[PDB]
Image: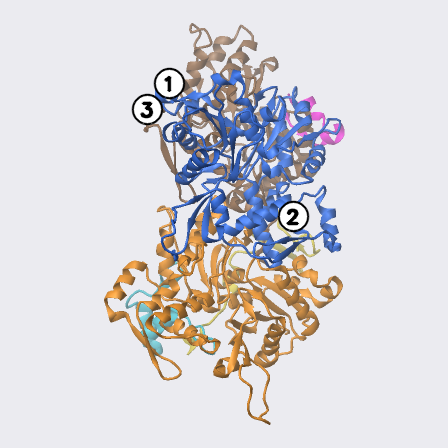
Chain colours: A cyan, B yellow, C brown, D orange, E blue
Amino acid sequence: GFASRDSDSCTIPPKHEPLTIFCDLMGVDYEEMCHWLCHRKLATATET
Amino acid sequence: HLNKCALFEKPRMSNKAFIIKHFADKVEYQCEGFLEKNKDTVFEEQIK
Amino acid sequence: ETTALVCDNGSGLVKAGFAGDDAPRAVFPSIVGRPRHQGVMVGMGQKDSYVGDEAQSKRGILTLKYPIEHGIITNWDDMEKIWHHTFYNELRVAPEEHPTLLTEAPLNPKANREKMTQIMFETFNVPAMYVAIQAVLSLYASGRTTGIVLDSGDGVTHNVPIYEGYALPHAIMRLDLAGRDLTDYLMKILTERGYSFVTTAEREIVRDIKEKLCYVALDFENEMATAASSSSLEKSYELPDGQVITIGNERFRCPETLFQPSFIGMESAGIHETTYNSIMKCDIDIRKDLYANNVMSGGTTMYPGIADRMQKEITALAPSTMKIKIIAPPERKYSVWIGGSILASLSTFQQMWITKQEYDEAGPSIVHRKCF
Amino acid sequence: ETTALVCDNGSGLVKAGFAGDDAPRAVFPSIVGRPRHQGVMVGMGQKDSYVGDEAQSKRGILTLKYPIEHGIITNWDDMEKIWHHTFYNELRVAPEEHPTLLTEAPLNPKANREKMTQIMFETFNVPAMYVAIQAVLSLYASGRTTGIVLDSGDGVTHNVPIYEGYALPHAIMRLDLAGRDLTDYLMKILTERGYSFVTTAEREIVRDIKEKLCYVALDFENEMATAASSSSLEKSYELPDGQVITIGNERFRCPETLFQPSFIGMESAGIHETTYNSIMKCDIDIRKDLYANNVMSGGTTMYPGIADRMQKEITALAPSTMKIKIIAPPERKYSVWIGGSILASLSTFQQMWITKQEYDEAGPSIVHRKCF
Amino acid sequence: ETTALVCDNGSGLVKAGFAGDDAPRAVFPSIVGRPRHQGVMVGMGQKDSYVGDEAQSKRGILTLKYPIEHGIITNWDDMEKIWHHTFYNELRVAPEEHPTLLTEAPLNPKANREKMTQIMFETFNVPAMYVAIQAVLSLYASGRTTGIVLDSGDGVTHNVPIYEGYALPHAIMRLDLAGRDLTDYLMKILTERGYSFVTTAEREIVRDIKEKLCYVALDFENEMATAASSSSLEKSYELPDGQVITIGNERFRCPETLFQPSFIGMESAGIHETTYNSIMKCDIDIRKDLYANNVMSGGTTMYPGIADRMQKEITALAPSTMKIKIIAPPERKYSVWIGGSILASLSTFQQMWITKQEYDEAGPSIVHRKCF
């Protein structure tokens, strides 16, 4: 469950248990999922 | 479509539903929540 | 059993709901909006023209038309949209299912009923219809059968004298000065304090300033002196663009002109003298009951302090040995609709309707036959 | 499918690619190279003139011409070489096969559209063509339907107000400050530390110094005092020749001419003050959503801290009852092209094209008649 | 006997001279100039600001301010420099010696009347003063006692209808189309042909194109088809730098906004419907005499072909059995000055002046009491 920081931004609350349990189960870094669930990457061939 | 087509009709008491003369019968569909069901976008970095 | 609709087309607002409700289902400004600006985004799902709260919400894109002036419908292609929206969208009721009760200001043009009748039976296909003078319903709502009724809305104000449900057609006075002409006159004074309003899309702000800020003078002429002395007389209000306005000597100079119509170059007198002259046309047996039962009605009467000014200025012109009472209840914006809600629900009323068969036999003139 | 090309003539950069992509395939300077010396060898396999990435690479031998200046195409045979390079060399796709969408700054000279059109239909034989205002595309990209769009490229700067997809033509502001005249100013301030750049072949180095080092002060005179007192702000850059230059306060003076155009001798107001004056030209009932929805767009908006400078210095011009918001997405350097990549993909848009078959009937006068 | 001065605050020009004389002695732009650059010659006798013909003559080096917008003074110290120049240099007479007369737009903001008054009795030391509604002076000037006046200058347009020397205050339409907004629109539309104008000094150059090349169509759409089919209508004008421009269908599209304020994004209708609707506010005894006696006022009514276009387009709205004649005297640019000049020369008028003793006894606030 995401917290709206702003109308154009959101964040996962600190040490969120559902994400913690998901990262433990799936074997992924909490910080990577926490970053990638709240941000996306655009990329032209020269820049991202 | 409302006046341009013979098979599309508007439910007399609403602006949030429409009627299609399907093969088997006229069917009234309610417009609420189609857009949210219609949208899929998976951020590739999450897959990665 | 199928209840009839009660639909006070009025002016400025449309008021609608079912007979037997205690408040209307639908209350919205009687307004049709068209876009004036260039359509530039593509695929926006634009709509040609707007009715009611949509036209209010989006008013900055639009030119705003009221189709009704002085209780006359003046554009039928605009007016039909307002009823269409009223029945199908806003009440969510098919007009073809059940009868309709409709309202009109007295003395208005003979063709207006013929066009309404033609439109209700032919175009909307209502099974049966009746038309009732707004002020008569204000008696049914105020729980009374003897009165003089001042119904004073947007668009028009009128007096109808009634004794025990007998109307006095020689004694009806009508005046077309009303809440909309306080809105247009409030523009013609606001221009002194440098604030600006010239466009229809911002006229609806002037109409909203009036509703919040204004009050009725017990006397104008000492308050006219007062505003040279007092800043306690000024108030401030936040516009939509975030500017603060502050307003002084306006708040008794424009909203009070229903009591002094000389200001705008017309011959006639205000609501006080037409109320008293409507009593002077009334029969001499009854005058104590009329002066006791003045009923105030409609949204333009909603001001704090209206009662005491009406009481004062009728007592100043009438003999003070007669007694004056002004009935101004807290419901008073809706009484014209409330009266239609009880009246249309009486089993005794059910005989009165013009049915579609009678119109299809007689033509549109039949209202003049079977109504007042 | 034959998808349309989106080909952002802009000025100084071309961004090109296929509709539905989220970024352009091709990003190259819209720049024409001719060799300035007499070419000395014989039998070399010499080529007359160079476009884009060639003209960046070889610049010490070359004359650089921009065919596009202040959103006006000024040399049609050179512009035709850039389109020729764009279709045939850079996208490597035949223009007779697919539609193309082209972009324009608002309020432009009429013959700019017409020569763009005739050249597309005769010489490239394009099957279908359109021109769309650069700022209008930006909203589709920034995900809104009500905004004012600060769109500023190399060529030109403009503000366009849009409220729910009606653009408001009297309030569209255009200004001739842009990424090129900030760059030509960056030369006349670099001269203060003795460094010199006077030739077309080295102007593109000043343009790259500008991109990496520069940033915006939230308030000018206290940072101007700060970097005049402390060397802690200064940074160094290696020229191509291996020479080091070093820069202090000067790396925040070049964007400040956007906010104070008297520094380059203009009367007109620059970017915060024209953004506010553009909002004031819309009527009052929509102004609050414009104050909520400022969208930054195009490469001249990329400076660090300019988002906070707009938010601060509009808050000085707006009333304190507001909420003032700057939307400054990181992708924004491409947002005009991204916007066209959305637009040319909308199904409702497909009716809109000028086809060659319509142009062959109507002549080059068609553009204003059917198109945007 | 003591003659008054008459001084038309107007907008865009001040027109001034001595009572009873047949043209103003002083006719100059109501304009104040300041330098924008850092000054490079030394010891010159440089000056704080330039007023009138000097600010026009030096215009490329200066930024030109009008202290008047929409007939409202918004910058008081510059207007004070215009009056200061007017008495001491331009009419060349000491302002204590004999009275001075001032002109005002109807319906306008309160603080303007106190600044107009106080500055004349205190600072310029005038012995006696009056402030007058502009359209009334245009009839007193023109040799009529009954007329309808479309009164339309730089800054502002309004109607006041006048019957046998009685003005009709209820009857006002007010509109902001004017000689300045035809000019700013003429910049923003000549931009179609590639020409560009961005500074106060060259808005005033387009203002001279407007005077010479423009004219008003008897019917727009056939002349629009004519100049779209044949190039034969276009004519050419010499810029100050010696470049020649050429103008075609444009030279009637900018003045035709007087008949379509939708061209500049106003809601309200053009000068024809404001003339007709201003008669419609009148009672039925006078309407025929007002339909007959149409008097144009302010210089923005001067274009060749405008009189016959008014005669057509009011006859299209008025009952065709009524008679329309357009009274367009050659003086009409000056008529507000002429009317105050001859009115002020009548021996019977001399009792009307507000004397310095009345201001000294009452304060300035008698103007709100004794004027309109």
Quick check: C304 above or below C78?
Answer: above
Q: Nearer the viewer, mark 2 or mark 1?
A: 2
Same subunit, labels 2 and 3: the answer reads no
Question: Label 3's element?
Answer: loop
Nearer to the camera, E72 or C95: E72
Q: Residues in magenta?
A: C351-372
Judged left or right of residue C2, residue D217 is left
Q: Residues within 10 Å of mark 1 (few under 14, many from 20)?
A: few
Nearer to the camera, E357 or E27: E27
Same subunit, labels 2 and 1: the answer reads no
Which residue corresponds to mark 1?
Answer: C222
Q: Hey, what amino acid is under mark 3?
A: Ser
Spatial separation of the CA atoms under disc 2 and disc 3: 56 Å
Q: Are marks 1 and 3 in contact (CB under 8 Å)?
A: no
Q: Which numbered marker is on residue E213? A: 2
Quick check: E106 above or below C63?
Answer: above
Residue C4 visible in the snapshot: no
